[PDB]
Amino acid sequence: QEVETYRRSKEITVRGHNCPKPVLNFYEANFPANVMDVIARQNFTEPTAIQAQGWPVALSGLDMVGVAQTGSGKTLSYLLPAIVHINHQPFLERGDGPICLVLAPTRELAQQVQQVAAEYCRACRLKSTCIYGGAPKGPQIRDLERGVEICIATPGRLIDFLECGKTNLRRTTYLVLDEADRMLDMGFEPQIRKIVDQIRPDRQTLMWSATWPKEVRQLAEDFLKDYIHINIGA
Ligand SMILES: Nc1ncnc2c1ncn2[C@@H]1O[C@H](COP(=O)(O)OP(=O)(O)O)[C@@H](O)[C@H]1O
């Protein structure tokens, strides 16, 4: 396995049934033209180790957990397959909720992901929005009502909105839990549960974490299906 040479090099450990081979370069991912336009402008030389192994897993439709240090490039690891997903699901109709739901523990990390996502949404003509607590409800409710394919959210504000019927998850087929361990450290487990229970069963779900403790591992087993576990580090 040329694979095992590459994984071993990049300190990639994979666990679970039938993980696809890692993609050795950007071109092999076969992301659509508009996304490539935006990737070329970032002057990356190469895929990061989790993009390498993570992308093909995500693009295959499989559930997974990606464990890597802050800075290993996981945002793109779930975002970019999200775009492909959206391209393969029907067109967004008046009043449809989001197709892709990215949950994040804090306002700041929610906004970071919106920032990364902005350029690709614009190149791909997708609409997205950052939902977070503390800030004016008005603009956020506007965005959700005009319709977004992508909704990046912190749990509390999302709940409030669902309960008020200002959006809904009956189209959410691609679920992301960024910074899951932090999300659990800050005590959001009941809230994340209350959220997912409203998500139709055929969802692909992807968790991302810098660490792999008991609490997170248990969340994975309750929420994921036959998941792949990717580790990055010695
Ligand atoms: N393929 C790549 N090559 C080089 N840098 C990248 C690549 N993908 C992402 N980056 C950059 O690496 C940094 C870390 O990305 P990020 O998604 O924040 O990682 P994490 O979420 O693991 O902390 C960002 O500044 C991002 O622009």
Image: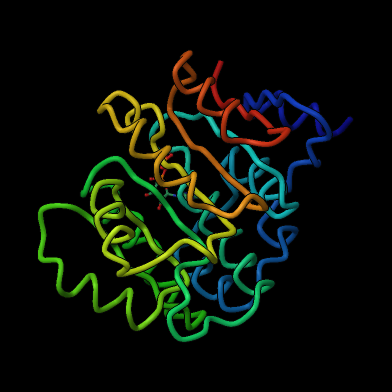
Q: Who is closer to the viewer here, 178 or 74?
A: 178
Protein image colouring: rainbow
Q: Is residue 205 toward the left or the right of residue 103 in the image?
A: right
Instruction: Tell me, yes or no, if residue 36 can be seen here.
Output: yes
The percent position of residue 227, horizontal first and vertical second, equals: 68, 33
Residue 108 image position (x, y, % from top left): 21, 48
In the foreground, 166 or 120: 166
Q: Could you tell me residue 26's position as x and y percent?
A: 66, 58
The relative height of residue 132 versus residue 147 in the rendered view (above or below) is above
Vertical position of residue 63 compared to residue 226: above or below? below
Between 37 and 174, the residue placed more toward the observer is 174
Which quarter of the figure has residue 127?
Answer: bottom left
Q: Nearer the viewer, residue 91 or 42?
A: 91
Q: How many marks?
A: 0
Q: Is residue 4 left or right of residue 134?
A: right
At which x and y percent is residue 201? 64, 50
Is 145 displayed left or right of 73 in the figure? left
Q: Tell me which residue sits at (71%, 62%) in the image.
A: 27
Q: Quadrant of residue 139?
A: bottom left
The residue positioned 60% from the left and 38% from the top of the image is 49
In this image, 158 relative to 214: left or right? Answer: left
Residue at left offset 29%, top offset 62%: 130
Relative vertical location of residue 57 with respect to residue 151 in this rendering, above or below? above
Can you say which quadrant of the picture contains the N terminus?
top right
